[PDB]
Length: 142
Image (cartoon, rainbow, N blue to C red; front, side, top):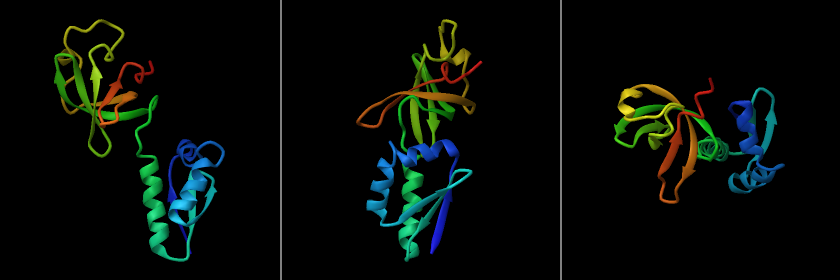
C-alpha cells in the first residue's frame, strides 16, 4: 500500500539531500519506495505497514536533526550571568550568549529575557557531546 507524511516544502530539501543523495540512503535503510508530491507531501510505498511506519518515523527524525545556520522557534527556560537557555524540540536546551540577545550592549540578560517566553533562534555551533550555542539576534529579522 501507500502511506504518507506531509512536511513543509523547505524540508523536502533535507529529504532530497544533494540531488537524491539522502533518497538513496532512505530507500536502502527503510526498504521502501519514496515518491514525492506537491505542497510538501512524501508518499511512501511498501507492501507491509511496519516498513512504511518506520520510514514515516525516519523522515520525522531526519528533519528533527539540529543543523548549523538553521532558524527555529524556541522558548527561554533559564537566564544566567553570561547567557540564556532556550529550549527547542525534544527537550534540547541551547545556550544563547549575552552578546547574542540584541544590537545594543548587554549588562544582564535578565533585563531582556524572563522565563516562559517564546523567542526565535538560529543555531551557531553544535558539539559532539550534544551541547548547543544559539542566537536570538540574527533570528530577530527586523
